[PDB]
Image (tube, coloured by chain):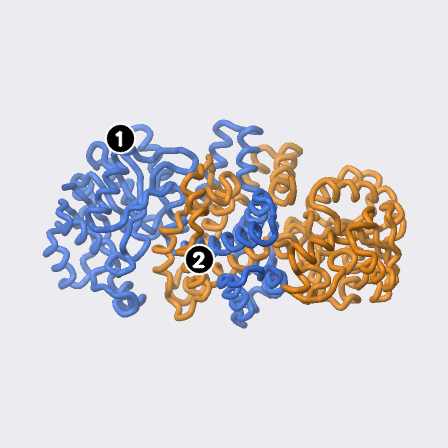
Chain colours: A blue, B orange
């Protein structure tokens, strides 16, 4: 049994009407934060749900939350005192950071604080870092990311943030094991993933990840089995294309990156790469690029390709450490990681 | 009419046997460099072809080259003196750079030197830069990249490198206009593309570009039409996923990046993104990820996720300029652009 505090019930009007989820995906309301609370309560845990606004959910939905055994409070500090694990199902932007900052002072010894989809745990860690580093060295940052809308049938799993690909531990092993056991007790598959990459595998952007990965693996097969390109050459091409596309969107936006890449041209080039006898990814892609929206094509036409300095980012991280280093290098790196991960502003 | 010099006939055994092109794509031999020479000669241009090794092509294929009106020399310096435009259909690695360095001394005033698929024009420019900057300020670097194997039916176009996304001009407008007119006279579509990105749209890696772009545009549609996510949020997710994937391959290789991303997990997450009623790219991707080669899965299992510091590269370029700047910043940037673009080593 665990003490669990969940923050934010979920905008039910959004799930129900705007996304039309009960019709499009399945399950029944409530969805989101309250649904996670329900599930944790049903797992036999001691669950508190903090929600300042009782209007975001029908009274009948409230009843289902309480019926599950969840204690509903409107005071974040009260949930802060309760939980050994704290799950922020809280709005995009300032609100998440305000709540985290509010509870950090009050959570009990060794509590772990977890993001869901509205924030990166790396950025949440940066926002609490002055506190975590002085007054609350015991508190962990992790994630309890559903990577699905809780209450829909797609929700069979949780993404939990562990040690970053840089080796930084944001939470202890104990803390991470608690989060894992929480996900499992609710009948979900638990995935521990490096905390920096959790967003990449769990947010709505995971559509891009999965499509891009499929193109990489397709290219890897052609390169190994048909062209016989050395491993390092295939990797260099992989890095060159994805890094260029990322950096073009970073300076110029989706429209500007499309202006630079030219989909018309891309159809021609990528045609020469039909070398295996079924490449469903390539076929899909060529089709999609052939049928660009006429008004998208019109934005693209008029887009500016802003100044872009195309570089291998890890090599540039290496350069800044050995050339300037110390506190100024760390400052540059934290700002640039923040530019990468920060969800809203 | 133009004087044109092409370097490298093309390994005919490779196109014919190893890639089985006449059977798989069409056309007739010769393919490659000699084929470009043939086509330029047929366009009514004064064409020289430099090839040190007469064994790389059957005597009957040689005959077709000469029959077209191409003058065949085995001396690079002799082709160097001839051409106003110089097309390097030359091997991966040292050989391309050795030839470029050999001809640079001898090409006539205002000549333009062009890469094809074995080299990036940015890296070719770096290798000649001490010369281009002192003795040969008149010489241009561009590309004449077929983005297809010349002699196959897929070859209907040329990618020509113009001003870089950073604003650097590697060749004059005159020089670029010559290259364009060359491509057109051969009946090809001419695409002028920023020279830094030419590789990304023209090399074998353009498979990854086209697949990844299709996932980006799919995600852009869901985000605009279904989720109603603000434009900047969609872009931030786009940057975050592609930049992470690039940098994971950069430190850890394809196997290590797949170990970090977890395709099993990716199937689950990306499932929640089936929101439009036909997403052929997503469907292809989920399929591909479900059916990973058993021995690929085994490499992935044992792969190391090396230290990776996940950052937005353009933001980090901005940091190095304002923190250190000058000659040390330029050195760091050139090395990191070189790490990105360099095809072989």
Q: Is residue B328 placed above or below A251 in the rendered structure?
A: above
Q: Position of residue A107 (x, y in %)?
A: 21, 37
User: Label 2 to label 1, Cα distance in Å?
Assistant: 43 Å
Q: Residue at x 54, y 72 (%)?
A: A294
Q: Nearer the viewer, mark 2 or mark 1?
A: 2
Query: Residue A33, which numbered label?
Result: none
Q: Is residue B109 visible?
A: no
In the picture, measured across the screen, residue A211 lies left or right of residue B90, that is: left
Which residue is more in the foreground, B16 or A217?
A: B16
Which residue is more in the foreground, A98 or A255?
A: A255
Q: Is residue B186 visible?
A: yes
Q: Which residue is mark 2?
A: B288
Q: Residue at x 65, y 50 (%)?
A: B196
- SS class, disc 2: helix
In the picture, measured across the screen, residue A278 lies left or right of residue B144, that is: left
Q: Which residue is mark 1?
A: A138
Which residue is more in the foreground, B285 or A151?
A: B285
Q: Is residue A133 placed above or below A345 in the rendered structure?
A: above
Q: Residues within 10 Å of mark 2 (few under 14, many from 20)?
A: many
Q: Position of residue B260 (x, y in %)?
A: 42, 43
Q: Do the residues marked 2 and 1 share a common chain?
A: no
Q: Contact, CB < 8 Å: mark 2 with mark 1?
A: no
Q: Position of residue A145 (x, y in %)?
A: 31, 49
């Amino acid at each position: 049994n665990m003490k669990v505090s969940v923050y934010g019930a979920g905008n039910q009007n959004l799930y129900i009407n705007k996304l039309n989820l009960p019709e499009k995906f399945g399950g029944e309301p409530p969805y989101g934060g309250s649904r996670m609370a329900i599930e944790f309560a049903e797992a036999g845990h001691d669950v508190v749900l903090a929600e300042p606004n009782k209007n975001i959910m029908s009274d009948d939905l409230w009843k289902k939350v309480e019926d599950a055994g969840v204690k509903v409070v409107s005071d974040d500090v009260e949930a802060a005192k309760h939980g050994e694990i704290h799950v922020l199902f809280t709005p995009f932007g300032k609100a998440t950071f305000r709540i985290a900052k509010t509870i950090i002072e009050h959570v009990p010894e060794n509590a772990v604080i977890c993001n869901t989809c509205t924030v990166s745990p790396v950025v949440l860690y940066y926002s609490l870092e002055p506190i975590l580093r002085t007054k609350r060295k015991d508190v962990g940052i992790s994630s309890m990311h559903p990577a699905a809308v809780p209450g829909t049938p797609q929700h069979g799993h949780y993404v939990i943030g562990g040690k970053t690909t840089d080796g930084k531990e944001l939470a202890t092993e104990e803390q991470i094991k608690k989060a894992v056991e929480l996900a499992k007790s609710a009948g979900k598959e638990a995935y521990v993933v490096p905390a920096d990459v959790s967003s990449v595998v769990a947010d709505m952007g995971s559509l891009v990840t999965a499509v891009a990965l499929s193109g990489v693996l397709d290219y890897y097969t052609v390169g190994r089995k048909i062209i016989n390109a050395p491993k390092k050459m295939i990797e260099q091409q992989v890095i060159m294309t994805l890094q260029t596309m990322a950096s073009l969107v970073e300076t110029s936006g989706i429209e500007g990156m499309v202006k630079a890449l030219n989909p018309e041209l891309l159809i021609r080039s990528a045609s020469s790469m039909k070398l295996l006898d079924r490449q469903k990814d390539l076929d899909a892609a060529l089709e999609i690029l052939q049928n660009l929206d006429e008004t998208l094509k019109a934005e693209v036409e008029k887009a500016e390709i802003k100044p872009t300095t195309l570089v291998a980012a890890q090599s540039l991280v290496k350069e800044i450490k050995t050339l300037i280093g110390g506190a100024a290098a760390e400052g540059a790196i934290k700002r640039s990681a923040r530019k990468l991960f920060e969800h809203a502003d």
